[PDB]
Image: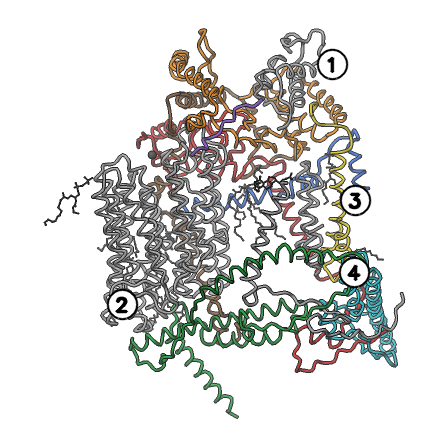
Chain colours: A orange, C cyan, F brown, G purple, H blue, J red, K green, L yellow
Amino acid sequence: YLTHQQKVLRLYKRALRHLESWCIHRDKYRYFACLLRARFDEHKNEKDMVKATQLLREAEEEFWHGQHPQPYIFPESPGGTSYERYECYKVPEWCLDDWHPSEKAMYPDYFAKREQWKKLRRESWEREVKQLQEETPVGGPRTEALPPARKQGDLPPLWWHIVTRPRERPM
Amino acid sequence: MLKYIIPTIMLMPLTWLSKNNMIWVNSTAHSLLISFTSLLLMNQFGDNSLNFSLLFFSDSLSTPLLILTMWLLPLMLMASQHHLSKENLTRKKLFITMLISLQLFLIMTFTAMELILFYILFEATLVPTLIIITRWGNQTERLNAGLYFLFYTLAGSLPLLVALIYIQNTVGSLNFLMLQYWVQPVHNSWSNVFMWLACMMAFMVKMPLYGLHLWLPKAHVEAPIAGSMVLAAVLLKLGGYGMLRITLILNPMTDFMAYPFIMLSLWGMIMTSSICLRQTDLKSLIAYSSVSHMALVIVAILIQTPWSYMGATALMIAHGLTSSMLFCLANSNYERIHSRTMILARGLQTLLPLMATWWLLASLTNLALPPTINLIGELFVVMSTFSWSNITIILMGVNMVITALYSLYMLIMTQRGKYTYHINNISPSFTRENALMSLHILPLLLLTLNPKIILGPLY
Amino acid sequence: GAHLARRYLGDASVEPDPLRMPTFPPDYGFPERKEREMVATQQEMNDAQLVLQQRDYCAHYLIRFLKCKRDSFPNFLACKHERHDWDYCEHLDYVKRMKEFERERRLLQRKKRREQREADMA
Amino acid sequence: TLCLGAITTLFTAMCALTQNDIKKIIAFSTSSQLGLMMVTIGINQPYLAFLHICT
Amino acid sequence: YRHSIFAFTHVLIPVWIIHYYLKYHVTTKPYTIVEKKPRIFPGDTILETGEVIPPMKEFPDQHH
Amino acid sequence: SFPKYEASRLSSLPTTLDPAEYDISSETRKAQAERLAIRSRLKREYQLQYYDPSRRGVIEDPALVRWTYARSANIYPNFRPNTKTSLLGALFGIGPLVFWYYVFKTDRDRKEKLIQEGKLDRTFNISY
Amino acid sequence: KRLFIIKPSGFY
Amino acid sequence: GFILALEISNMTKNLKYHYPSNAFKFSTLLGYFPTIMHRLAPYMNLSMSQKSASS
Amino acid sequence: SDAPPLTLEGIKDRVLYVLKLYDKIDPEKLSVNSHFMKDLGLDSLDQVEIIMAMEDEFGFEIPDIDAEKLMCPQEIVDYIADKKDVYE
Amino acid sequence: HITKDMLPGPYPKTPEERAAAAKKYNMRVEDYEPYPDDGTGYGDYPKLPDRSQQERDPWYDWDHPDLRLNWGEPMHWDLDMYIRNRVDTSPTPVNWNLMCKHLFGFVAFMLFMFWVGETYPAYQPVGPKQYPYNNLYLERGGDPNKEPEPVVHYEI
Amino acid sequence: DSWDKDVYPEPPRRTPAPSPQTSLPNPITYLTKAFDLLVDRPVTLVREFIERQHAKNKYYYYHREFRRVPDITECQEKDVLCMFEAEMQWRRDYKVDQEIVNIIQERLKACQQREGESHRQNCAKELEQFTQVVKAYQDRYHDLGAHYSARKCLAKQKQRMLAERKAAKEAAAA
Amino acid sequence: TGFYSKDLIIEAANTSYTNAWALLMTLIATSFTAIYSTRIIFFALLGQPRFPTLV
Ligand SMILES: CCCCCCCCCCCCCCCCCC(=O)OC[C@H](COP(=O)([O-])OCC[N+](C)(C)C)OC(=O)CCCCCCCCCCCCCCCCC
Ligand SMILES: C[C@H](CCC(=O)O)[C@H]1CC[C@H]2[C@@H]3[C@H](O)C[C@@H]4C[C@H](O)CC[C@]4(C)[C@H]3C[C@H](O)[C@]12C
Ligand SMILES: *C(=O)CCCCCCCCCCCCC
Ligand SMILES: [Zn+2]
């Protein structure tokens, strides 16, 4: 979940972003961005948690009533115009194993070096499994975070599909 | 018809006397030659049909069905080579023998001049079809699918046997040429009301008619690919072909007995087309599309107009090449991911660019994009039903909207979007698979240049 | 227009009815009227292929304008005078219609004006 | 057709008054002009509706 | 050079085929190409028969 | 001041206006972390196969095999012919068929009467 | 800088 | 329209605050037609397809 | 898409260039390794604005789950370089 | 391979079976709630919240980024209706009931005014346009044998 | 020439003569000359070459003629041999009558295009001829159904004749 | 270019036996055409930059 600290920061970011949409012009935004910062300052160091929640809970209602019906969204962010625009050009790396040798003959250096990575992934797998079979509690993982490499020469467990992932502009 | 019956029979010795590694090559090559000679049946006249002998005749209705039937055997052999590679040689040759027997019965069925001869051959197609589903299907449900496909057809066919034998005792003959001249009107009585049901229930169950279609989503889905192709392309058209013939001797009782079935089909169109919008199994979505396309055929045949008959014949041929193509396209995915779920493998257009082109063309024909013969047949049936009752345009129009939604939903759900990350065995499309699709869609589009040869006797 | 404010938001008997006009016979006034003089003939308009709504009493100028436009090609800026002639004739034709509306407008005043005397008096 | 076009040319023009996406402003602009084309067909001016298509 | 080649393979050859098709196959059948009869105005001469169309009646006067 | 938000089946209540989010107690905290254990336990089983370099195929998803089975094969054995299902199947199954029958029989009966009387225009109607 | 474009096999 | 638009656009540079009306949210969200119909009709149709026709 | 590719040096220069324009940061003691909370005395409310200024600089949003985890200009460079495939 | 022991079954009655169902669907028994046993065929499939996949977190590292699903996660009974290409349930800035009234009010009001404007048409103050002899009787499809009623137009 | 002008009439072609009233050249005049030189002349040379070869190997094809045979009214009930020949004859006539309606429709369509904006008055004869052939076609071939036959057409005719005879009496009733 | 079609339409719409409300909506829609066209000019061409620093 989100602690009370995280929920306040998120609302502050949303409040400024929607406010930026209403203001448009930078100078006007730089004015109401400071005034809105002040409203987050008059209660910066509240002590009573119950009072703090009632302040946060009331801010959300004012945010919902005041949010821009059509807020600005970055082009590549969820709901943005360019969101997932290049997901059709993102091919995985395993499709190169199905290439004809004639196609591979056009890139002798790339595929020679790609073979080295496949060897590196293949040699380090059995060690990665153990690294997770020992740090895991008796029952099973209680969180989604993976541990780093502990011994020199080892690679971070479960690294292939985050390291070899397609680029953001594949073509 | 002995110039086609005998060569088909000789495909059996060829398969059994061929080299072990040439069974597919030999059978495929000579089944394409028999398909080539089938074009000689196109020697049609504007007044008289081809009446070969006392047993077999060919007219503008049976001829396109004969050509389609003989064209599908080579395509069935291509589609089955992969999943039967790890199969006993004798059992591979028995699978081909069942396909050859099915063609042998079908070509004699469409040309039989005597109705009882038609009945026996029409009924003999169950045995090889039943054996293909239950022996070479993959899932457990193939056993239950075979039982449903078997007892739905015999529950309607057996009353047809009594009705046909009754007709011969009263009319004296069942030769279809004789009936054209000795036919008499059907007086409105309770006895004739049941002669009408007995003479039409067998064909409607095989069409199938909405409400009696529960066998189709089972059989067409659980059958092997070759079974599904013949099941949806030629064996649904035995019911339509029978009704076109048998309706000659049911007038005028058809003009009021048709209402309960015109209503089931018109409303069944919308229900079956709607089911496809929520189908999880890709092969099952294609199966229900046939039910919705054969609904138009039933309506066209029952309203008995020259335009409805011309549309019905074009629809049966057009649907034969499109549904068969869709099953092969679906089976192409299954042979890689070994699952029929539609949402399992996605974004396949980024991994199989050319196979996504076949999906597009197969989807455009299915939703009746003009001027494909799919639209010509469907349009001709909408025109005729409008004259029947102008309100029918509402039901026909709604089905067109739903048809486009589930045709493109299938295309979008399986080809577009992001690919599934953990599916990494999508090998490039084989030449066999690509050539199989080209053998479906190219004839389907070339027919647009000369539509008249699939418009039936009423042309 | 101002007339619409009268036929709807006020007395409607004195205002003309555009769908029914004209009501009074053409000879109510005008001891003698002259029929409109159609310069063009039926065969001329028929052979010129004028749109049926263009075959009005101004058609003779339209025929001349079309002939000049065909001959003046490729000079599309020419035949400027012929166009204005046809436009002006259509302007005069429109005014006659405006006069017809006024004639019906005033003659309906007569009924509402020569009927209180014959009603209030008796 | 006159009433169908009249509501279209108004409703879509009113939508564009507050859209922030440049492509959607020009998109609703097309609907408004298309509405004015059907208003032209409603007043029995087919050749003015065509001339507006070209321009 | 490139434009001249394009004007030969994409305009000249196609128009030869289209003209041949229309000249000897498509215009030899009835009612295939139907031309709206050309307009005739008062005072025109018909090329086919040398006929003369009488001018229109005198326009009385408008001036303005 | 600030009108309350009224949700709908097609407009869910925002998470920032839901009381259950701001009423954090001990039981809720344990439940939230107790769920995250399952998500991680499943996420590990998937990853040990997704990242496996010798695997080539499809990772079978038992959740996906339960969904399709639940929608196709598990429907009939869990059906009881009661008042709710019988009336729903009667009016949605038979109702439309009877409705359309009378819409068409009435339409064709009316049309046939006019044709016999000779007062239905069929001047150029020679395509049927 | 002339990177390698990963695409599915186009030979077949 | 130009004069009104000039004044309306000029007011956006004033340092006043925003008071979102209901006419503003009506045009911004396209009259709610894409928010209702595209959520209500697909829901009604797709639910009928599975619960009634299919199941 | 015809735009110049980003460089590791360029990201660092522009990340610090933005912080140099933040009044509550002293340019003298600002370094790539300067922790915001424990070396510049900025509250988290100020760190949110720091991230919001970075996303307005490179034109792409940073999710709140990861924005609240960057507490140093060097980390911002790593995050931006990893999300733009910048390797040299 | 998958066995009958891990496939959906009948509605759970005893609390022993409810826990087994929850363990089968990878849900915590407090979160597991089957559909009401009304005889429509839902069996023991969990009744998950009727939320679209557009409401899921778009920044989480889903195993199925487009579907916004994780391997092993139980799927909503109507998942294929809630994909991002279909029914959306995300919160709206305006209340659902308020939106319906404003849309219905706009459509209803405009239709009434079109009817009002239909019965009170606007027109220019002119008389009927006059066409030449017999209102172009021959030109617009008149029988040349039947004599038309003379149509005569005068001048003002 | 290629087609008979009695079955596909084409009115005389009156083309107005050029009468330019401008100094600028007419682009169509120069383009017409270019078209004739570049397009029409090479095309003719190819056709003349092809036409020359046909004369060297000239052969003929003929139009099949069917002698009339007894119609269905002259066949005994359930006599297949006589009914067969009557039926195949009624089908050929049905097809020919279908093409007769096609021809009159082509006249109507060609007249409307040819007369331009005056087609309403100038295509009154074609419209009338289309309204009579359509009436005749509808009488003998409408409402027969997909399984039409000479018997059904004969039955339809005898139902119309009874209706007309029943109308003559009620007409001569005063 | 747009004057030779749009203004003939608006002129012909006014002098026609036409629906009154459909005429009013058409005229109001012409006002809105200037407003949103001015919106693009003002928010994209005039004023000060609001786009990122490196463009
Ligand atoms: C003549 C009637 C024919 C009957 C069919 C038409 C009636 C509507 C029923 C069919 C629609 C439902 C199909 C299933 C949904 C499949 C597509 C889908 O999932 O939708 C998701 C999409 C959602 O797309 P979205 O753009 O709205 O939002 C998606 C989320 N974003 C935008 C963030 C990406 O919705 C649609 O595209 C379908 C909208 C059309 C359905 C409503 C039709 C209204 C018809 C007009 C009503 C007024 C009558 C006017 C006169 C015309 C009538 C004669
Ligand atoms: C003339 C045109 C562009 C020239 C220009 O504008 O600069 C060039 C660009 C590519 C060329 C075409 C392509 O090269 C493909 C063909 C190549 C052969 O020269 C035959 C014609 C052919 C079809 C070419 C015709 C023409 O020369 C083209 C079309
Ligand atoms: C009248 O001709 C109808 C005009 C309808 C469009 C509105 C134009 C403005 C009319 C104002 C009335 C002026 C009266 C002096
Ligand atoms: Zn396989």
Disc 2 element:
loop
Place of residue B74 in the rendered image (x, y in percent of width and height, measured from the top left): 32, 46
Q: Residue at x 78, y 40 (%)?
A: H5
* Camera-side mark, 2 or 4: 4
Answer whether residue A46 is visible to the viewer in this image.
no
In the image, B276 versus J44, the foreground residue is: B276
Residue with the mark numbered 3: H1
Q: Which mark, residue L1?
A: none
Q: Which residue is mark 2?
A: B175
Residue I70 horizontal/vertical position (percent)? 60, 15
Q: Which label sits in the foreground, 4 or 1? A: 4
Give the alpha-carbon distance from disc 1 to disc 2, as whole Å: 103 Å
Which quadrant would the N terminus of chain B be assigned to in this image?
bottom left
Q: Callout 2: 10 Å neighbours few (<14), some, many (20+)?
A: some
Mark 3 touches mark 4? (CB < 8 Å): no
For label 3, the SS is: loop
Marks 3/4: CA–CA distance: 42 Å
Discs 1/2, front: 2
Tell me the subunit letter for badge 3.
H
Q: Badge 1 is on which residue?
A: I23
Frontmost of labels 3 and 4 is 4
Q: In whole angstroms, how far apart are the C-alphas of marks 2 and 3?
A: 82 Å
Label 3 Cα neighbours within 10 Å, binned few <14 / some 14-19 / many ≥20: some
Q: Amino acid at mark 4?
A: Ser
